[PDB]
Length: 61
Length: 61
Image (tube, chains in turn orange, green):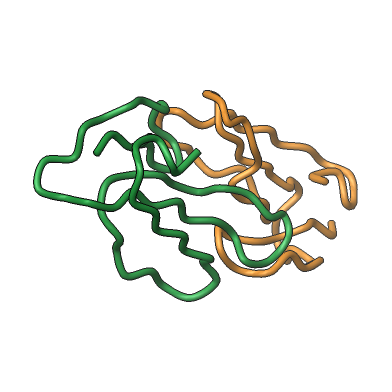
């Protein structure tokens, strides 16, 4: 499964995710509402974050 | 000097900044290009961040 990936500061790339089936998109739940991170897997997320986890290639754009 | 303030996850408020003359806006230098934080002062910033520091009330919107 290929997923977009980046931290809040790093650059947005496309990776393969060995051993994972999901991709994630973390976003700010409160305005500004924006994406804070994308990556492999489905991490547990701290408060204030909306977490979306999907299973097809490139689904986390 | 009153400045907007928030972390990447906390809520956006308006604060007074005792003892500071500047407000800051941290942003992502690389796309998505977006604001990651606002607050009192002019902090030193890690790589990948565009830092703007201003001196009038509410200048960091």
